[PDB]
Image 1 (cartoon, rainbow, N blue to C red):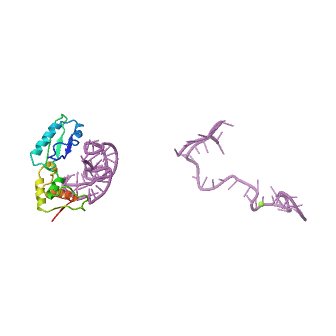
Image 2: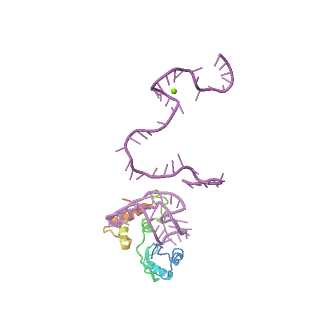
Image 3: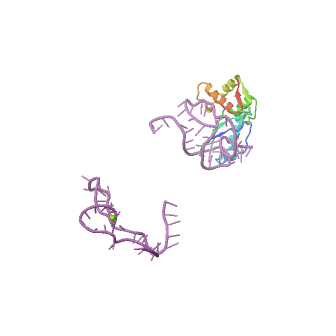
Length: 140
RNA sequence: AAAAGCAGCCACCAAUUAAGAAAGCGUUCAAGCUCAACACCAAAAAUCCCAAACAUAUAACUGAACUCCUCACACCCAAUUG
Ligand SMILES: [Mg+2]
């Protein structure tokens, strides 16, 4: 019916997360990989991009890609790749306010990513809480 | 190389208008099914089980050599004794 993937854009086509996991349901991996590579080339690579693949009963696909994620997104915005081993103890990310405003503004895009709130405060609160759960803390 | 929500540890925020970084079930692994919440909502052993038997007429009856009623009283213990 519907599957949710998070394979990295730059990553061409692995095996487990796109081979047997999908073969059990019968698919055409060629077209899926081609569309994924096209969407990856359409924008700078090196960032995960979710997707809402719509598996039709006629063995046809209609991929629906979106904006980057939140984990790696904030990890790259703060400047640290690997996260903390124990949070919130092992602090790491220390983001200011202007960067948070900018990242929230550029994230406020795809409606499929839960954008049922008119103001942006409610939306940015979610990513702020997610960062708090991570080894990142909001400065100022 | 993997556990993403349950091989192991951390904090467990918070957007859905209004509620789990997940309380179970099932997944190598994700897939699927529920829940927390919201909208009216005790019996068994060998000859054969063993007293008939009734729930609905007024709390009181029956029941000794125990006590009493007429008379006179020494006349219900092993061994032993007087
Ligand atoms: Mg007498």
